Length: 116
Ligand SMILES: CCN(C(=O)c1ccccc1OC)c1cc2c(cc1N1CCNC[C@H]1C)n(C)c(=O)n2C
Image (cartoon, rainbow, N blue to C red; front, side, top):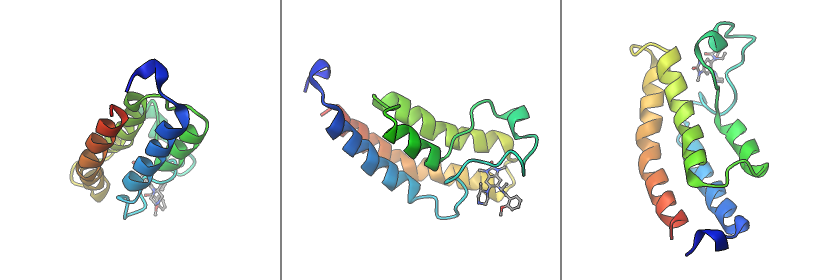
């Protein structure tokens, strides 16, 4: 399977499935819409690039993820943003740790498929 020959549609089908699997791990509904700046007024004082699963879905369908690195980078922002903004004694921090853990095998297996 050679990179210049790779078709977009199959790759996007793979990313759609992978994103569904990742988002399903958000059983607390913490990561599935943007952190609202109106309700968390200091959020952008700390976080340079917010990310969430709905924004990832929009990016996917707008053809913004054309390799696995860029996709995984945004999933990793969901986690890292949360670990920075929230203290390690909070439920939200631990929820990000759990999301990273559960996302791990999903992403590794998905990348292996993307590399054929
Ligand atoms: C701003 C929403 N939020 C809350 O914790 C919250 C605040 C006020 C009133 C109700 C609320 O939720 C019930 C929130 C903050 C987050 C946050 C997520 C949320 N909410 C929790 C409720 N579901 C939506 C989600 C965006 N993440 C990932 C963060 O890093 N921070 C700081």
